[PDB]
Image (tube, rainbow, N blue to C red; front, side):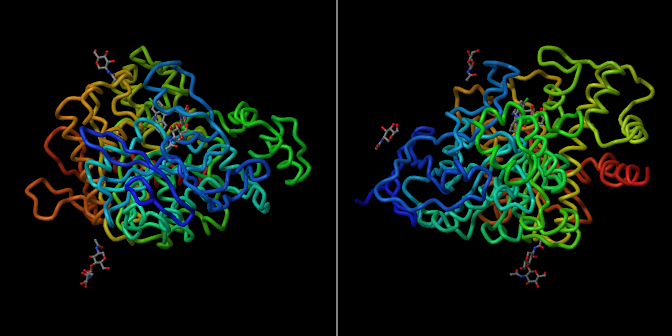
Length: 534
Ligand SMILES: O=C1C(NCCNc2c3c(nc4cc(Cl)ccc24)CCCC3)=CC(=O)c2c(O)cccc21
Ligand SMILES: *[C@@H]1O[C@H](CO)[C@@H](O[C@@H]2O[C@H](CO)[C@@H](O)[C@H](O)[C@H]2NC(C)=O)[C@H](O)[C@H]1NC(C)=O
Ligand SMILES: *[C@@H]1O[C@H](CO)[C@@H](O)[C@H](O)[C@H]1NC(C)=O
Ligand SMILES: *[C@@H]1O[C@H](CO)[C@@H](O)[C@H](O)[C@H]1NC(C)=O
C-alpha cells in the first residue's frame, strides 16, 4: 500500500481524500485525532496523546465540533450562521485537518490555523476556514486544529490536577506537538511552521509565543485582531476559581471541596453547563467571556505584562494587525440601541450606557475620562457620531490598543514585526453598513474565498485576497511578507522608532505610522493610571 492519499505517521496510517479546488485538485486529510477523547473522567483534564491505532484511519470527512454555545440571535441569517458549528457537537472533538498540495511536496511551509470565538466557541470545520484555496494557491501545507472551549477547555481550580485550567491551550499545544512530530510525512517542513489565528485564536498565538512549554514547537506567528494581553483573554486564578464555584452553584452542585465540585460538574450533560455559563460573569458588560485562560504560574510563569517587559518570550518574526471597526460586532449583540436592520443612531443616553457596558472595570471618574476622550462637544447629539464613537471605544479598548501594546513590547526583543490595518468593506457583506469592517471579516480574504466566482466578490477583491494570501504565505516561508527583488510596493518592517504599518485594501499600498496612538496612549497609559490612583 503506497499512494498519494495514504500517509503513515507515528500514530498510524491515515487515508485522505482528493478535493477539487479552482479547476484542480489537492489532498485533504480531515478529522485526524491528536489526543484521547477528553470524555467522562477526563472532562477538564490535560489532554493525553492519542493512542496509536492499527489499520487505516479514515480521514475523508470533517470531525465533530467541540461542545459550545450556539448563536441564535439571527436564525438562518448567513452572517451569524457562518460561525456556528456546521457538524455535530461532541466532547470527542480533538482532531485536526490538513490540506496538502498535489503532488505531495517534500518539505514545504506549514501554516497552522487556530480558531477564534472568545474561548467559548469556534470550529475548525467552518466554510470560511477551508484550507484548500490557500494550500493550493500558495503551495503550503495548511493545518487546522481544534481545542476545547468554554468550561470544557478553561474551567480552572488552581491547585487541582483534575481541573487545573488552560487545558484548551494544552489542546492546541498537543496538536502543535503532533504537527512537529508528523507533518514531515505529509510533505511539510517541521522547521518552518507558522501558527496563525484570529480573535481568541490570535490571542492563543501570542500565548504560545509567551509560554516556555510551547515556544519550541513553531518557528513564526501571525496574530489577526487578538493579542494575549487583551482584557478579555485571561483571568487570575482567584477569578477563575470564583467562576468555577459559581458555575457549580448554578447547577445545584456541592461547593465544599474541589473534588466534590469537579465530580458534580463531570456528571452533567454538556448542554447543562452551556445553559448556565453566561451567568458567572462578574460585571454587566460586552466583549467579556466566561471561561478563559488563567495566569497560573505554569503555562504562564508570571503576569503577561512582566513577561513582555523582561523579554520572556519567543523571539522570532511576527506579522499582525487589526480591522477598522472591531467594536461593531459586540455592540450589535450586546449593547442597547444597536440593531441589525437599523442604522443604529444612538442617543446621548444609549451612549453613556454603552460606555459603562464597554468598560465595566471603570469607576465614575473613569467613565467620564472615556466619554470626554470620545465625544465631539461641538456636536454631542449627532446619533451617528455617538454610534461611531462607541464602535471606536470598543475596538480600541478590547482589540487595537492591546494589540499595539503587545507590538511595541515584542518589537523591542523580537526579530521582525510586520503590522497591518485591514479597512476594506466587502462588496457582498450581509451585515449592515454601520458595522463597517467587522471583527472576523478579514478571514475570508486570508483563506481565499474571493477567488471562488459564485461567492460574488469583485475582481479587485480577488486580487486583494491573492495579495494577502501571498503576503501571509511568503511570510510563513521566510519571515518577510515581501518577495525579494519583485517590483511591487514593499511592506516595511515595524520598528520601535518609526512604527510603520500598511493598510490592506483594494487601493495602492499606503504606509502610515503610529496606528491610533492618541487613543492607545489613553487606553494603555492614562486610564489604567487613573483607575489605579482612584
Ligand atoms: O465571540 C463572540 C460570539 N461568538 C459567536 C459569533 N461569532 C462571530 C465571530 C467573529 N465575528 C463575528 C462577527 C459578527 Cl457580525 C457576528 C458573529 C461573529 C470572529 C471570531 C469568530 C467568531 C458571540 C457573542 O455574542 C460575543 C459577545 O457577545 C461578546 C464577545 C464575543 C462574542
Ligand atoms: C534577526 O536576527 C539576525 C541574527 O540572528 C539578524 O542578522 C544579523 O545582524 C547582525 C547585526 O546587524 C550582524 O552582525 C549579523 O551579520 C547578522 N546575522 C545574520 C545571520 O544575518 C537580523 O538583523 C535580525 N533582524 C532584525 C530585524 O532584528
Ligand atoms: C470513510 O467513511 C466515511 C464516514 O461516513 C464515509 O462517508 C466514506 O464513504 C468512507 N470512505 C472510505 C474510503 O472508507
Ligand atoms: C450571489 O448572487 C445571487 C444573485 O443576486 C444570489 O441569489 C446568490 O445567493 C449569491 N450567492 C451567494 C453564495 O451569496
